[PDB]
Image (tube, rainbow over all chains, first blue to last red; front, side, top):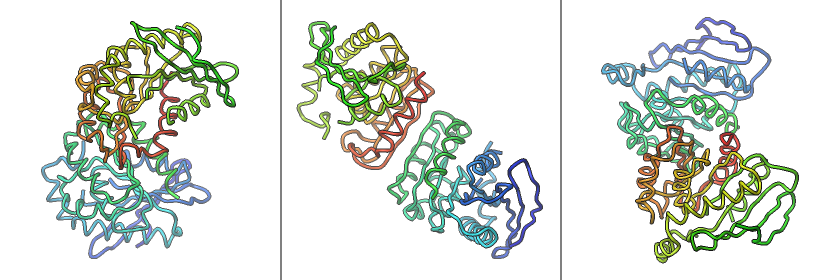
Length: 222
Length: 222
């Protein structure tokens, strides 16, 4: 529950590191914001592309924050299931992000807040959005019910009640299309839309990952 | 191959009727255009919502044209399969739209041309786009492989090579989601994106049907 981290300043984006102590764990984080003056909305980024998204969001006057989770793509590694549980799994993720958002709200003031995160970002983001009603819109994707925390995802999906845009890749070698569909179907909200594009897990079209998601959060996050 | 039809003028949109004689058939049509001066792009509209889309397109400086095909939604009617075949089926649709586009091109000058059409509009549009390479982008949807011309759709889908946005409704009572997915998967183009929203066949969200499709064609039709 304190800055540093250690902080820099790249162009018109101010980046500040922070660190949290949560239920016995050390939680490293980063906060991106306009270098002057203020910023009226916030997005939590779950995970290079994260830094890219953060820059674009700041460009729309939207601050961004990320912490590390219990984690080509890490979810495809044989060692990944062990890493996830050793890191406290879904319950730890929920508490860590709740503590991180508490911190930012006290330091920067509470603002309309969204979630952006694909793959492990959805393993984290779907539970967080279900659990923390401060999340007013979520961009999720590249994850299904056969994920490492699939049980939790299926259980918590009906409790996602905010608007969602969900991305899947048709030829995703890590997440079958059917598994991704099953999870999308379980989301509680009626204000959900699924975009599916051709290609492998890492091949979300850039206009979908960048312009598309940033426009979606910019429009829907109020 | 002549105007009338019989024509009116509503606001800044000029509407002109036309009529064609094609391989023994009488083909009724409508042409929407800016009332002054010109318009550099055209969209063929396959089918109230058609008139709505046409108005929005004209607003972006995009003219629109529609002819009647061999046809709540007509595709759900027990009499519909008979009507489709009695109307010459897919081969008749292809020739009729080819003749209609020939007519407009001679009268108004050839322009970058797109396709918009859902349900019966895709029963017609997918074959037309496959057959007529003047179609440079297509908005398709609400149709699958279990459609009345499903065989033709499956056969011709690999020959759709232009960009496509495809819409499906999760709870579509007329077109199963799986049938819609199967057809989307068969489209030849790599520049295709599927948007799926919750609800029944008639419940495409208005922001998806209007703003979304018009923005898509406006951006992609060049």
